[PDB]
Length: 147
Image 1 (cartoon, helix red, strand yellow):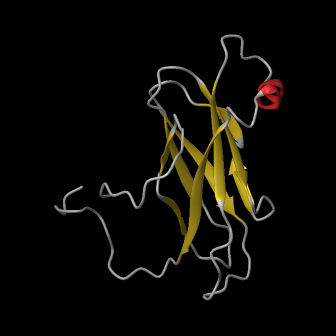
Image 2: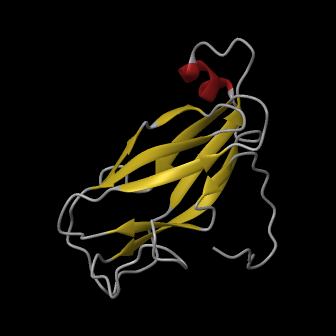
């Protein structure tokens, strides 16, 4: 990884998505895929996140929601259903993750996300990149061989 932002835009987010740039997907595509999404929480208070994508039919996220403890990272399992992938596919699909702090009496989630207004709810624009398993050179470390 290497710090590098492309353009300055307006976005108010508290939860640091990982990868924050784009979420790569290890193929193949002709079979069930498995992609782990890391979600870092810099804040020191509970926060609720709602996983929502444009292709909820070809995507299986679990947990599909929940709260990320303050100062911790969560690993979400995003399984991609096997479908006819095209090499000349267009950049349409998109992944939008919603995040919002949790109340002191956070009991019913369905009630929170509901009461929450679209003017306070924080979201993030992310793109899912489909990669192929066809590796070129085995990788173990970015330096030494040991371990």
